[PDB]
Length: 225
Ligand SMILES: [Zn+2]
Image 1 (cartoon, rainbow, N blue to C red):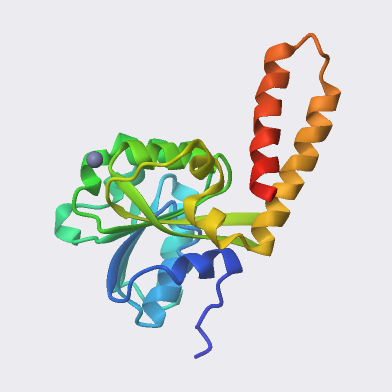
Image 2: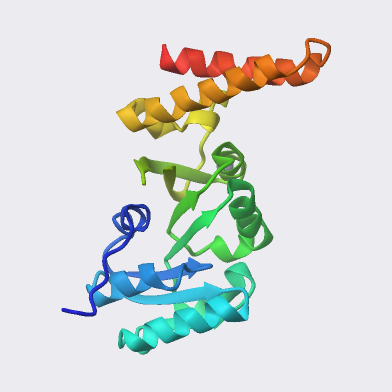
């Protein structure tokens, strides 16, 4: 079908983790692409594209309409998780293309609303460790992770569950550590390089800034060794 869309790798790898038949909220949906993909293929039952300001809201609305999916995809202008209600019967939430602190904040601000959500697929752009820390502290459990190239992007798949993570697992990812893929090694090899430039750029007097860097460097050296 000519209106079928092909997702970016990043968004495709998120879509691959959305359960069949899901009723999905995509928070700050990227032009509603991901909900359109999932609905046009019949892989989900229903979706909401949640947008925070008028431009993106209008974009998603137009796209859903053009793709002939207005009956199956709601587009809403609402702050974070306010984009859904009990009556919507959402079981899955995706949040992509934002920093890990921001994702954790959106989740924390509306934590009560997650009570009936079964699965989250989260694609942080950075500060992944801060998102992992928030998940661990709030009775969420990571059940799968992926790292992909396109930049490298991490995807975390989450369900309710009590999880304890080590500092290493928080920083590197319990599943990313275990899978230990080439992409993973390349990401951390690159961080090592940057941190090594950073540490040599800072004066010896700045003991605290240097210590922070030394701590990161050693962690990485351990993982890579
Ligand atoms: Zn607990």
